[PDB]
Image: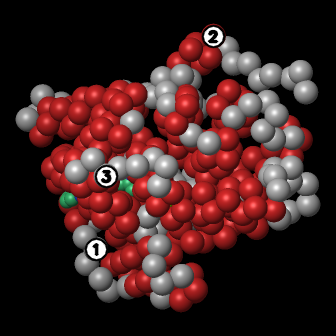
Amino acid sequence: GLMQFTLPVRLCKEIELFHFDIGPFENMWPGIFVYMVHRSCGTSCFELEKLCRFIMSVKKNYRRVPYHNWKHAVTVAHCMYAILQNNHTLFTDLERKGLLIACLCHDLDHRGFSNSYLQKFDHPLAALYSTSTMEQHHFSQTVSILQLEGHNIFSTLSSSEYEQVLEIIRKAIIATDLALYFGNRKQLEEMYQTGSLNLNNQSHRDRVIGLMMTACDLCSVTKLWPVTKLTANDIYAEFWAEGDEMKKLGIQPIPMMDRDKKDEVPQGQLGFYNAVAIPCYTTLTQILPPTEPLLKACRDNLSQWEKVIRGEE
Ligand SMILES: CCc1cc(C(=O)Nc2ccn3nc(-c4ccccc4)nc3c2)cc(Cl)n1
Ligand SMILES: [Mg+2]
Ligand SMILES: [Zn+2]
């Protein structure tokens, strides 16, 4: 009850910043997550024993893939922590509870393959979930783990509060399907510009949380350059393995996933910054002004990819 997690001084200070990198010491990541729940939510939000058991079963259900792994889960949860801590009074008690868990769980049991690849392979998951295939699976794995004996971290919530938190988690996890991000961001653009955006309107809050989820999910482009550039290698290690698997089904993959087209990566990163990342953080910054550092860091990385193209690195 009187038992805080504390971090060494460098981590205690830097964990508060958006560009924080959780480090290569896997055994410190559970403690970093508990630290973030305790400061974001409270020491009372969850029974410590249940939370620790939940975290460790979540870890066990992430796979040893190059990018969509336990380190990504915790990294996406830290970006949500930073957003929440910089927007103290905008979010409900249930939202603070749900969103860190949603982020920890958002890629549960990812195999390193896109929704597209599952549909072309004709994976059983693509017949069970026709759109947002992996994201409905991630939500299903989250409910599975919440239902294991001793793993119900929400046990103190009423029936209707429990239903509300699981609904916040479902929508937050579905929103990490980047196919749904383009339309969500356009509606948020129109709503903000015509002044109709209303944070008491639940369907509006849902949209804003969806955009927060995209921003956290993509937060590798908001790190200091050496972190962003080394993370890119892990992202492409998966894309290129998917490319190989498309070639095995007799399908020329898109260039993004074709290892023969490594040379075109810098221009590919430019498209992604310009079509996805910058717009994401720009709209987030308009809605939630204290998230501006995410946008500033993204623009710094865009300018580094521009330097790569110009052979200045
Ligand atoms: C799983 C989602 C995800 C994706 C990315 C990412 O880097 N995306 C993207 C987008 C689009 N192209 N096009 C290319 C490309 C095009 C032609 C030739 C070679 C390459 N390369 C990417 C890379 C970053 C993060 Cl943080 N999460
Ligand atoms: Mg995902
Ligand atoms: Zn993710």
Question: Could you tell me how far apart the alpha carbons at marks 2 and 1 are, in whole angstroms?
Answer: 46 Å
Q: Amino acid at mark 3?
A: Ser
Question: Could you tell me how far apart the alpha carbons at marks 3 and 2 are, in whole angstroms?
Answer: 44 Å
Residue 227 location (% of width, % of height):
40, 32
Q: Which residue is mark 1?
A: 253
Is residue 189 or residue 212 the one in the foreground?
189
Secondary structure under badge 3?
loop
Q: Which mark is residue 196?
A: 3
Lower position in the chain sequence, tag 2 or tag 1: 2
Q: Is mark 2 within 8 Å of ligand 1?
A: no
Question: Could you tell me how far apart the alpha carbons at marks 3 and 1 are, in whole angstroms?
Answer: 41 Å
Q: Amino acid at mark 1?
A: Pro
- Is residue 176 visible to the viewer in this orientation of the structure? no
Q: Residues within 10 Å of mark 1 (few under 14, many from 20)?
A: some
Residue 287 location (% of width, % of height):
35, 40
Q: Which residue is mark 2?
A: 9
Please say if 44 is above or below 242: above
Q: Residues within 10 Å of mark 2 (few under 14, many from 20)?
A: few
Please say if 216 is above or below 7: below
Q: Residue at x 30, y 64 (%)?
A: 183
Q: Residue at x 15, y 50 (%)?
A: 267
